[PDB]
Amino acid sequence: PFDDEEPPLDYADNILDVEPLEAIQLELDPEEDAPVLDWFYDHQPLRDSRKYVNGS
Amino acid sequence: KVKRSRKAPPDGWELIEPTLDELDQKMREAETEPHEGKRKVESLWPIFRIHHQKTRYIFDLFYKRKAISRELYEYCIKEGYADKNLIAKWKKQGYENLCCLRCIQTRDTNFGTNCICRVPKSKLEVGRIIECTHCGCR
Amino acid sequence: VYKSTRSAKPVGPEDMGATAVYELDTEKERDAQAIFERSQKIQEELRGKEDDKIYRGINNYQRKGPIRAPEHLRATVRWDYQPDICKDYKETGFCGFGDSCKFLHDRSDYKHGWQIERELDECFICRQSFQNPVVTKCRHYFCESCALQHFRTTPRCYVCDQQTNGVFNP
Amino acid sequence: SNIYIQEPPTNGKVLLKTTAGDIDIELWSKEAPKACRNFIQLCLEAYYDNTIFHRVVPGFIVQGGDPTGTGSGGESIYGAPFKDEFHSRLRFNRRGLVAMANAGSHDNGSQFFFTLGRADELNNKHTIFGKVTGDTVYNMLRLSEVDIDDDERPHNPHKIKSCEVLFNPFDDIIP
RNA sequence: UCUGGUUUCUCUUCAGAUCGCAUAAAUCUUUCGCCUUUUACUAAAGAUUUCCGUGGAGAGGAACAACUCU
RNA sequence: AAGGUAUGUAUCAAGCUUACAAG
Ligand SMILES: [Mg+2]
Ligand SMILES: [Zn+2]
Ligand SMILES: [Zn+2]
Ligand SMILES: [Zn+2]
Ligand SMILES: [Zn+2]
């Protein structure tokens, strides 16, 4: 997706302040997907919550 | 600018946002400018300097002044506008005018010691105007 | 003067070419894979029909062929600079391998591509004013009285000692 | 395809009507913010009306934005001259590029220039802030007439008769 | 009334377990298969390693640790 | 990929190398 003789794009002045577009993110509704709703699309989903996961 | 928490952040973020926008613009200028003339490692002192002043602005704005609440303070840390680590070394007793975390790492140094930025100037020898080679000065 | 369309939308594609399509061959609906697919399909639909002779087309009387290119891939191109030329038969006229030599047997020393690239980047006797500049037999224009005094010196010329033979002209 | 546009996308366009025709310069506002703010601010002031193109090096550049017409008069909307804003994907590889004109250090004013060809000697020396939308690059190739009379400045240089702002990002007022 | 500790970071050996609810590459020894010779190879067996990871253990802190299991 | 367009000498810079011991 990039031509030759083009140095690979320099992440400071090129896409640092560019916001990303949108992820895939299938929309979950409440009243059926109520438990998983707060955390289901999160990098590690339950990470800082001692009730459901080990720890960090 | 990337915010990475989709939060619509709490209050009062609107009164620190022009300040933090100014510090980010100065950090882009202190990140982008060339390295000719600036010798080898004095061209990387200013990013530690402005990182220090950004973390210190949120530091004395929260613990000292008690203007910002706890939630927005934890927000500014968890986004990236502060160190989680360097305020934890600012809270400890003997050192809260600290330069940055490289003068505490005792195995960055070859002799197993802390850098001469972290020496009480009153009890060093009188005239030597040494600047720390890592962090920038004392 | 080319008048502009005067709209604020910029000049080119929105994706900035990130779906560039490689459309250098026959397009998808007219491609020979699609014609084969049409023939396959219509031979599948007419099966209970037995020679109703409505003819349908050439092929359909009863994915190989020219194969379709991936539209989403520019091919990585090099230059094959290294020519296959017998160095011998180019500069001598004799290869010891005869016609068994694996190279070309060419004798043309036309330039290569890279060579074209790296050229592509780059009076007078008395030394006075001409006081009657006057001539002799053989083009010798001298000043007049100065060449008379020259004849008083030597009867032949000054430029190449040619025989003036008394002849002196303007 | 295989052609690869190879430069960042634009935002904000200014149509600019000189006596050689209409030129629609579209700006890299994000990639060079202070210079594009300067240029739309001055075009919004109508600073550049009756300003001539006082230097043509045909094949290399054509300069403008001097309302005194000698090659030194430029007054930014910052008061002092401002900083150069380079970018690794904005280089002088082609015609149609528009760049502020510098005299050494961070000295950028109103005086800007079009390119007319390849200008690799100017890389990391001038702030590219806009390209020219095609079918109107020929109107600024009208600006390169071999009439130069000197090393610069031909007989009747083209003057900027108006300057529109077809799209205005980052809110402003004139003076 | 007294008893009183989960996280996170580094080391410390033991691993006998689907250490891994899946699964790489190498070396050697033989049989294959393409083969002209050699590395690139083939696809089966045997025995070995490397590598990406994990399990239980001693120690040092720091992280609310004083909330309180006990 | 090698197996073919040889290699072996004599003068002329950047590449790379320490930025040192020193009356
Ligand atoms: Mg052999
Ligand atoms: Zn310090
Ligand atoms: Zn420091
Ligand atoms: Zn120091
Ligand atoms: Zn031959």
Image (cartoon, coloured by chain):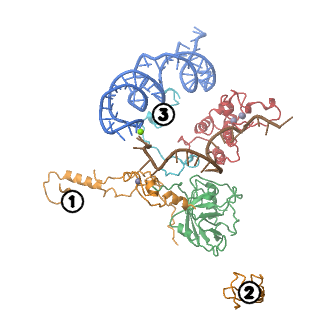
Chain colours: A cyan, B red, C orange, D green, E blue, F brown
C105 or D91, nearer to the observer: C105
Q: Quadrant of residue B58?
A: top right
Q: Quadrant of residue C152?
A: bottom right
Ligand 1's quadrant is top left
Task: Point out residue D26 in the picture as x, y percentages from the top left corner.
Answer: 55, 61
User: Where is mark 3, residue-wise?
Assistant: A45
Residue B68 vs residue A44: left or right?
A: right
Disc 2 residue lies near ligand 5 with CB under 8 A: no
Residue drawn at 47 percent across, 46 percent down: A22
Return the residue at label 1.
C58
Q: Are marks 1 and 2 on the same chain?
A: yes
Q: Nearer the viewer, mark 1 or mark 3?
A: 1
Inspect the image, locate mark 2, and give the three-letter code of the amino acid beneath it. Pro
- Work out whether residue D35 or residue B127 is closer to the camera in this orientation and state it: B127
**Position of residue C21 measured from the top left corner of the image (x, y, whole percent):** 41, 55
Distance CA(mark 2)–CA(mark 3): 121 Å
**Ligand 3 within 8 A of label 3's CB?**
no
User: For the residues carrying marks 1 and 2, which lies nearer the camera in this image?
Assistant: 2
Q: Give the secondary structure at mark 3.
A: loop
Does the image show residue B12? Answer: no
- Please tell me whether mark 1 sits on a helix, a strand or a loop: loop
Tags 2 and 3 touching, CB below 8 Å: no
User: Residues at marks 1 and 3, common chain?
Assistant: no
